Image 1 (cartoon, one colour):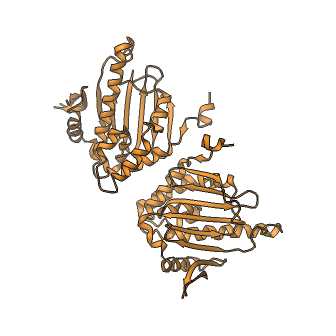
Image 2 (cartoon, rainbow over the protein chains, first blue to last red; image 1 turned 180 degrees about the horizontal axis):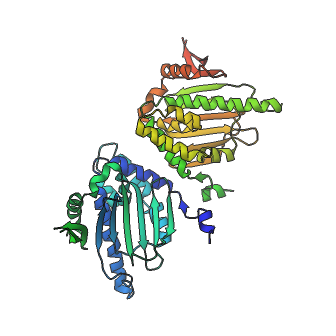
Image 3 (tube, rainbow over the protein chains, first blue to last red; image 1 turned 180 degrees about the vertical axis):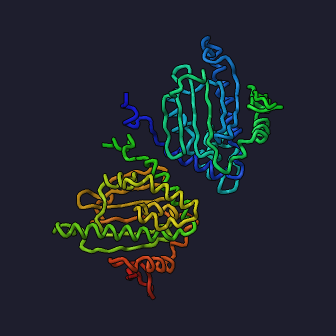
Length: 232
Length: 232
């Protein structure tokens, strides 16, 4: 089965509106980059509310993973930041549509709302959250953004992009998440500070204060043992 | 009758490598933006060379327009800069493929030399011309780039892009060029200087010196009379 790889059927271009939105976010929040974490944690919380709602009516909802958490891991050696939730997850089709295109039926209005909020010197920090496009703020600190996800209705898939295009492939590691999503950031050289535990704990603790689900950060304590530390 | 519009068959996404290339050009030449005009004049000359070579074997080559020139026009009120040549032109298929994708079988190595130059503080100004991707430097000064072209083997078409996507449509004005291409730039606000005659003349005069085709600028002379003025 070499049809898929040889035909590049795993490669996609972003919808024009998304390209424009990514640029708007990056040029508006250039001064407050740390907000990407708040947006990822917020998306995580939302994904967990969704599976929680589904579990109300679907008895098999939490079979792939019994917990409802958000776990963060800093891999300094690999220069990677991971944010994992055991939320509803996304199917292969959802990864392409939810991350590659924009809807909300208020795109143009928000498109003019973002620019106007950045030509008259305003804040776009609260706007991106409102329109549900916080995910893209990840590019403020990452050269590469990777999304591994497992939804009950599909097999585990990986989405990856450097903002100039994106690809979606079946995860060769198989089903490792159970259910949920991991956002993996390959940090820009200048964003290395986010590989520091103290910086992440302070930020996470700062943005986890109003999150109803438990958020942990893989951290070290004193020999030197590692384990999940509750932040909220 | 209106399938193209109802299906957006006229819209295209850029190839990934082109997105990356446009970014590298803008990130490394932000200091010497005026080079866009050198590149457009250079491409125009190359287009005139092509039709000249075709006229050697084809006696009907120049029937659509006998002259071999480059005519530049400033339109301050409309915030536009036009660069028109009577070269070989481009068919609809060439507009889609040539401006939307990249070949040369050396894109990879070039994107490496570009990024490398930005790391060693080298001059990428010479590099882009050598690889034949000078067209993209227009985005250094324009929010929108429009390409109207007429090739002997097709009808007049229009290519347009704000860099987040591009579309190609049949020109509803019909065949107004005869043969050739017009590059129209909708200038960025920070690029208003290029709407000033004295400035454009100074740049065209400088960049046209070694061009073997006459290059003109639509200018005024003391009543106030407007006409083409030879620059080389």
